[PDB]
Image (cartoon, rainbow over all chains, first blue to last red; front, top):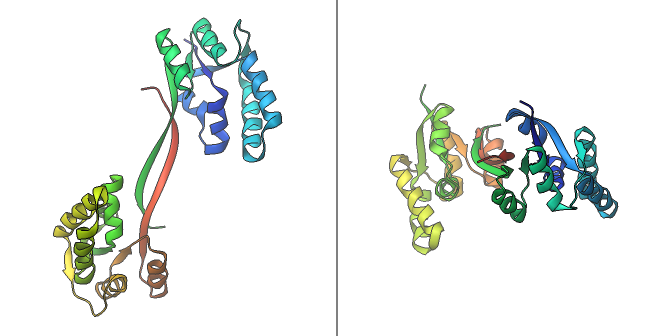
Length: 125
Length: 125
């Protein structure tokens, strides 16, 4: 079956800022549909207008990624809309926001988040 | 042939502090003899007596690792002794010390050092 993921825009900002291929990694786990809410997309467009430097670039890159997302409407606005969308469409919710993860857990919505693996290794080059 | 590595004690402190298996990683590259100088080993024994907390534990763990190193004598003392030993015995020198690496490079001694790889990935567990 077609599996979907709702991805928090703050996670997408990490694509540019940390060279993390979030969408490709989600595809490996079997997710082939990517959803955002109209509210959160609009909030990111507004945020972009006030960001500077590399954060501004990261928001623009996130906005380009969203060109390949489905944009869905919700009753609620902002972060709560991500939960509403994930539950309605039967998606995983990808976020690092601690309150969002808790609420999703409480509603039986599966969650994924970004983790950093640091390994120290011997370099001969 | 039997390949040898001289390993800076500051690198060995990272074994405990960062869970980096420096000796095992060196074995993978074909190094099966591990050398320290009498001077640097003694300096680490003195240092241990003044360290505290987890640094004290890391120095003790480094000292235990040195139980499986060959201890060799040199004319010189301290960091310079690591270069002297590496050149005499034909070893690679493993250090993160920028001056030590330069001097080794200038004398044709191969160098390895510790690097940190950070990858950001999607966690579903």
